[PDB]
Length: 291
Ligand SMILES: Cc1ccc(O)c(C)c1-n1c(N)c(C(=O)N2CCn3nccc3C2)c2nc(C)c(C)nc21
Image (tube, rainbow, N blue to C red; front, side):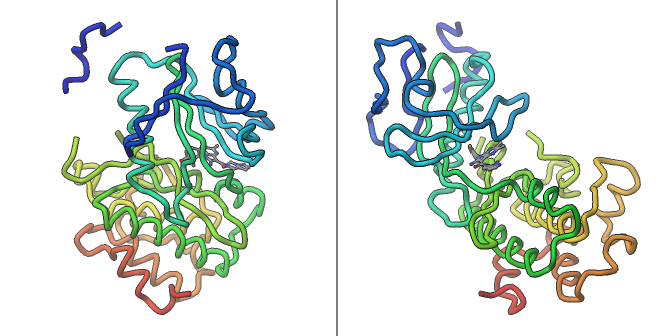
């Protein structure tokens, strides 16, 4: 109703977080007894390794005591600051669910809050596309690039058909599947056009400087994502180089080795004018991007 004015503006029992509807907020698991002081997360999972960390919190590789299967769990660092912070963190679950089952989107298994900490349990993926390129140590071969471009386009087509904008497409937010596949993840910044925060400046669509939000923004971000991985090219967060990449410039020092076909597709994705920029649907229809 109105975030920032709540009665009791100022929970040691876990509560399921869902905007889908199931009615059962109560969590249970083998290995979990709510009368013991450890959290649901502590009692219900074997934490195997830390996959990542930052200001947001941490991600663990875990084995579920429920099914013996491997998952990734992301947890927030600190208790919610208050109801706006809580509403903003929970909105990730709403967005993640709103996305849905799509094979090119990271699948959310369940989410819960406890002690003001938010936990999201997803499928365990492979490394991020950024981590993949770091391990590769060079430009990805185009055969790999075509598969990751297709997969991430399928993911964007799925979001965009539903009026959803990811707003933070980049190698760090794309995760390897088996067999040269990948999945779009990190729906924390996703917005629903015409309803109710900024992506990585290196990948940001030029029209966002004027607050012009649209699905086209994601196509531009994926353009620079693919340019980066295909050319092993570090993207500037600002200055002349940042501007040039938003004026149709492809640096010849990095891009001379691109196939005409991959170059042509990147030019359509990097079109500065969001009204002229190709849609994900339009790109997936091109014979060069089928099967
Ligand atoms: C948990 C979570 C909730 C929401 C959501 O949108 C996403 C995408 C995730 N999510 C995974 N599924 C990760 C993962 O599965 N891995 C990648 C890192 N990595 N390294 C080796 C294997 C892996 C396997 C993962 N990793 C990190 C560092 C972050 C920040 N989130 C990740």
